[PDB]
Length: 119
Image 1 (cartoon, one colour):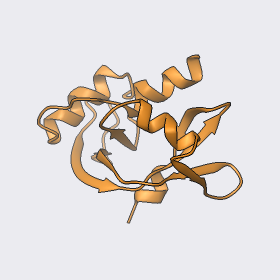
Image 2 (spheres, helix red, strand yellow):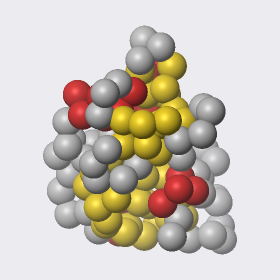
Image 3 (cartoon, one colour):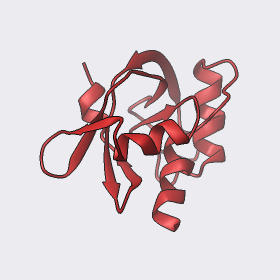
Image 4 (cartoon, one colour):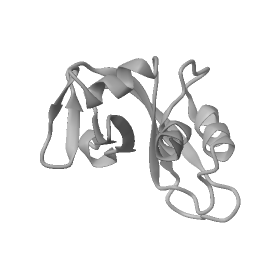
């Protein structure tokens, strides 16, 4: 399932290290989100079984197209240094523990809603 794959590439990291600014710049480059520099991108930590579970019992409908988790997830948000999308993409990290909102397709996560955790 490629759509599921793109999701894990852009939003998943089981065991992170540092979770600081340097973690974001390295990660965004490694996961290919610097062409162009993605504005905001969040990585979810933990296991993958719990993320897909949000598409099942451990989740609830959040509108017509999304699901919200029944429990919080450890997450790291990488925000672009809005200014200079040139090859060097600047980022700063922000660690949080929140309930998340994803989009599911046939039982698999396919999209992460960044605006839900803006506040």
